[PDB]
Length: 145
Length: 145
Length: 141
Length: 141
Ligand code: HEM
Ligand code: HEM
Ligand code: HEM
Ligand code: HEM
Image 1: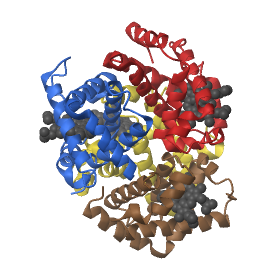
Image 2 (image 1 turned 90 degrees about the vertical axis):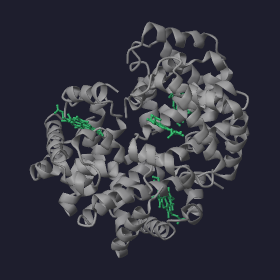
Image 3 (image 1 turned 30 degrees about the horizontal axis):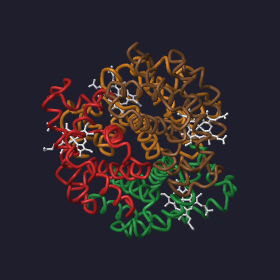
Image 4 (image 1 turned 180 degrees about the vertical axis):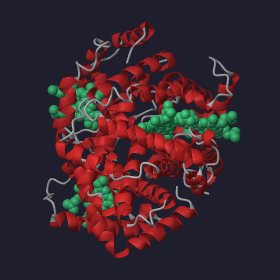
């Protein structure tokens, strides 16, 4: 997928103003709450019995930072993405056995997080850019599958 | 995706014994009957009001032979599939606007047609081979998307 | 299927939307057309430009239909039988499109009510919208 | 949602299956494990070899559950509440797997009853299996 100059702008503009700390666990928490079957992969994290327990879980917030980070590496490699996520594509495929369908879900939840943080600033034009990015990352991880 | 020698055998063995004539419209007919929203793309074909009208429709059977044919081209190019379906990938993407999700559906319906024709002969081992082929063709057409 | 908790969240959340239901419906559509342009092929008769009167008007129609589904959350098949005929029978809308509209609707609610859009509410609405979509894509008459 | 026609097809078709319901359930699973190996990770405690006694035994359990759903096609949520707890709450099965099992089940029926598996029946069963899957993947208690 190819990105226009206006699209690279919208993505990089927001990445600059966001809480990389707290926003990671926010996304992972929502994934586990809205799409319950995903808790099967994070069974080892401990207490995932309630929305409060999940969001309060220390290991969810920690892993959240890691996920958010790998998204920043994507913005840095917009022209050539596939080569950057080959390490994670193998990890999630052969090592974890996660269906690619779930990568799209995390991407959507990602877009919803940005909407709650930026409100009116997260315009339809800005959203279109992020959807395009999210779709590219999802299909980069599905190389093995 | 890579194919084993036993897998290339199972696929080519059945392609040899099948009714390329009547089996094309059989598949297209089932697609339109089981997944109704697909009739939107073949609106120009005429009467698609009932299972009898759809299966009896002359252009459904005609177009069916064409689809079955493009599947035969896949068996001959099991090594490098992506390059063979680039003409159709563009046609279905930018020209027709068909969601890739529908390619998987036609593939499944394809496997079900072979099951009705070969009965007992269509063993679990044979099915596994065909599922693999069907999945590859579906993702070959999704190059644009 | 919706749990009693889902029904409570959906009712409580839709109440907070209130008067702006029409303004939100218009925006969800504007976002969908922008983020997923292929959905534009379903509205050839529409002037899909920036602040179209048709789009803002259809947003109200879509919003009222949803307000109606919340009231009849226990009898959706019977209450939406008319819309099911339109989308499934006449128009023949591909179900994948419902997922796209549901997403843009959630995104819109998240931007205007970030405080109210808790993970718990998000989860219940997602399920609710999924139920509505199932009804509008099925031929049951 | 199922139309009255779907309910008739499902009842008529499942009747023709009859006694072999258990033999068909066993085969659908054998095909699924073969065609989609990732589904094997849900049965670590199972000996998944060729003619396993566990697999053939689980096929009967799965088949009986479906026979039960056909009888209670009008009250699936209440009749399958136990299985919904198992698959959705306890095991946490990814919904995509239900589509894979439903497919292999249809394929099995097509091979043993090609005469009876008309496009119309196929369509009704696909919908029916989709309803069952929705119930087993939802947390509604
Ligand atoms: C946007 C797509 C995704 C990205 C960018 C991503 C990123 C990552 C990263 C950076 C790690 C940590 C690897 C390491 O420390 O070496 C990881 C591991 C992991 N991911 Fe993802 N992930 C994605 C989607 C998913 C989804 C959807 C699931 C399952 C619902 C999942 C489940 C896991 C699990 C179980 C681990 C291992 C955790 C551990 O080591 O304790 N990932 N992922
Ligand atoms: C296994 C994936 C598919 C294959 C191999 C395939 C193959 C073909 C072929 C060979 C043609 C005729 C092109 C020509 O004559 O130049 C075609 C055109 C077409 N296909 Fe497909 N197709 C596939 C899936 C679909 C699906 C799922 C849909 C929509 C549900 C669809 C809709 C159409 C339409 C509307 C046309 C144009 C018909 C016309 O020219 O009158 N195709 N396809
Ligand atoms: C949450 C799911 C949806 C709801 C509640 C909904 C609601 C409605 C309503 C209330 C109307 C106008 C009915 C009337 O006044 O007769 C309508 C018409 C229509 N809908 Fe939807 N809809 C939904 C999803 C979709 C989707 C996903 C599509 C395709 C992208 C679509 C396409 C159309 C079209 C083409 C019309 C006809 C427009 C016209 O009035 O000329 N709808 N829908
Ligand atoms: C048509 C949908 C399905 C039906 C009717 C069904 C039916 C059943 C039944 C009746 C049992 C045994 C219940 C008992 O005796 O307590 C069961 C258990 C189980 N099911 Fe399913 N199931 C379905 C789909 C799936 C799918 C798609 C998966 C994952 C690939 C799955 C995984 C399991 C597992 C792991 C067990 C526990 C096995 C054991 O007894 O040790 N099921 N299911």
